[PDB]
Amino acid sequence: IDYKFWYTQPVPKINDEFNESVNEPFISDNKVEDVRKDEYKLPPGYSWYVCDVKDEKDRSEIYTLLTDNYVEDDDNIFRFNYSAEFLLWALTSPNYLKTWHIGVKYDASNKLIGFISAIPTDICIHKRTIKMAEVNFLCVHKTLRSKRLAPVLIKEITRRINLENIWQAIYTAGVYLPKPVSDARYYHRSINVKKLIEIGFSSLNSRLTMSRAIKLYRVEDTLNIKNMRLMKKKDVEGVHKLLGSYLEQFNLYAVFTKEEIAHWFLPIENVIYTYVNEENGKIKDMISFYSLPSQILGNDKYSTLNAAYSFYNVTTTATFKQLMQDAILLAKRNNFDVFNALEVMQNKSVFEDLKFGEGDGSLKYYLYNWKCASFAPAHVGIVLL
Ligand SMILES: CCCCCCCCCCCCCC(=O)CSCCNC(=O)CCNC(=O)[C@H](O)C(C)(C)COP(=O)(O)OP(=O)(O)OC[C@H]1O[C@@H](n2cnc3c(N)ncnc32)[C@H](O)[C@@H]1OP(=O)(O)O
Ligand SMILES: Cc1nn(C)c(C)c1NS(=O)(=O)c1c(Cl)cc(-c2ccnc(N3CCNCC3)c2)cc1Cl
Ligand SMILES: [Cl-]
Ligand SMILES: [Mg+2]
Image (cartoon, rainbow, N blue to C red; front, top):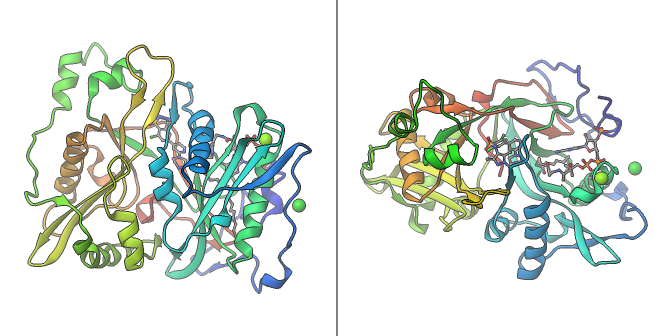
């Protein structure tokens, strides 16, 4: 595979190896003055569209495009189905720009056929803090694949991010591109095991009968940390200190302001779940997970897999194992079928004892225009949506 597009870009070549002594841009001294003011050209019959994510109709068009054309599993049974309310939350964080929510319409039918988006955040990479763009939800309609529209969308969002004097981005993908700074597998913890088997997400074996699998994944409906409760606005300062202080140990992590903590953590039903343990007016433990369902295609019984994805979890009054056992419990109480986590932060250490199973492939973390040492995923301290 040649990466004829990617090799024109400020990113590492497949064989590039940098020491820990290197931690800087590939291209520095960039000038907002010099950024191209013209939109990149689209094939005949197609146009840029500025998406207003706070307009329910524009949002619903993005929602439809992703519902029909986003990430599918290797066998093509499952397709991610981010909710409209989810997309609102994911793309209207503090200081977001409307002009980084970019669609492409096919003129003749006025239908949206392409999308890419970014949001601004401060990213600390090997102890340097850089204002970056966080790029997500790149999607080209399934009918228009391998026509090189993705590189158009990418060069256009790059241009619009550069116009804000920002020159670095972070992004994740399942595909291998030049070149991951880290690489983390998904692990899956079955909650509704019979449904997971019936939809073909998990399996059994003569060793393991349906009843025995159900017993294996059975959980006690009692928290290790008995006062774990939904987060509220009063807990923003406390979570800002607990999470902020925790994250500083990692090689890569978002440096959250208090406004960002409110946005990213305050709970939204069917979007984001954050629980806290408050002890003497201090927040001492937190659990958070987000809702990302998969549409189940062509099943007579089920149309939706409800999945909870581990987001940020910190404990100071229990073991990490006990905290994540509580996270699984909290996802079960909210009627989630499976709890997913990446082998980042301290997550791997709990996967065997908590009966997680290893997933297929992995999620690659990337930076744009940044040269640095790569590292093991335990050193990663950021989870993108
Ligand atoms: C300073 C600011 C900088 C801002 C930008 C930072 C960079 C942000 C980068 C974006 C981060 C997104 C992160 C994200 O959203 C989360 S990862 C999920 C991405 N979305 C999907 O998988 C949805 C299902 N697939 C599709 O919609 C299409 O297959 C897409 C649109 C993905 C590719 O459409 P297509 O019809 O299949 O392909 P062509 O148009 O013919 O394009 C082929 C070229 O596309 C390169 N490609 C393929 N998949 C990619 C991927 N996931 N990242 C980056 N590049 C990807 C590919 O390597 C090749 O270049 P090469 O010839 O060099 O290999
Ligand atoms: C049930 C189901 N529904 N679908 C759609 C799939 C693929 C599955 N199978 S899975 O659950 O076992 C699983 C899971 Cl959770 C996640 C990844 C993974 C791979 C690559 N990229 C991303 N992202 C890209 C951008 N940020 C969002 C995450 C996720 C792969 C698998 Cl295979
Ligand atoms: Cl060009
Ligand atoms: Mg294409």
